[PDB]
Amino acid sequence: VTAIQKVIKNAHVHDGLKIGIREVIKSIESQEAKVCFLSDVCSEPAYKKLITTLCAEMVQNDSKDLGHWAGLFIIGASSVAVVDFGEDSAEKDFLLSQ
């Protein structure tokens, strides 16, 4: 769980985070979103279904936590989509391997 925060920070630093539903969807529909952090605790789980199917063609808990991790200082995030990353080594070699 602590291996995600670093990645998010790196993404923030090097400009490429599609944060919040529609943007995430757009990123997915095209070869840009290289990893998708979504959530479990939602409403309707229709969102979740949409995400999963799109991925198929990480999961994780809660929205507030995601918002905190994302650039909001804190409105509900729902889903994040990372492009570019911006660095290597340390805790990216863990999470990716896992």
Image (spheres, rainbow, N blue to C red):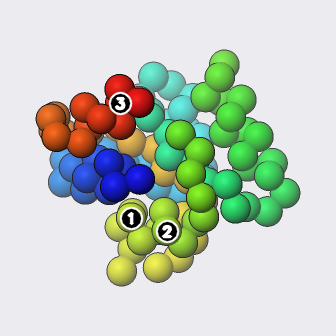
Q: Which residue is mark 3?
A: 96
Tell me if mark 1 has few (under 14), some (14-19) or many (20+) residues whose alpha carbon lies within 10 angstroms of its own: some
- Specify which label sits upstream in the sequence, 3 or 2: 2
* Nearest the eye: 37 or 47: 37
Tell me the mark number nearer the camera, choosing from 1 and 3.
3
Q: Are marks 2 and 1 in contact (CB under 8 Å)?
A: yes
Tell me if mark 2 has few (under 14), some (14-19) or many (20+) residues whose alpha carbon lies within 10 angstroms of its own: some
Instruction: Describe the element under mark 2 as helix, strand or loop.
Output: helix
| Residue 90 location (% of width, % of height) | 16, 40
| Residue 23 location (% of width, % of height) | 52, 48
Residue pushed farthest bottom?
73
Residue pushed farthest right?
44
In the picture, measured across the screen, residue 47 lies left or right of residue 85, that is right
What is the CA distance from the residue labelled 1 to the residue labelled 3?
18 Å
Residue 23 in sight here: no
Give, as a three-letter code, the residue at label 1: Trp
Residue 66 in sight here: yes
Give, as a three-letter code, the residue at label 2: Asp
Q: Which residue is mark 2?
A: 65
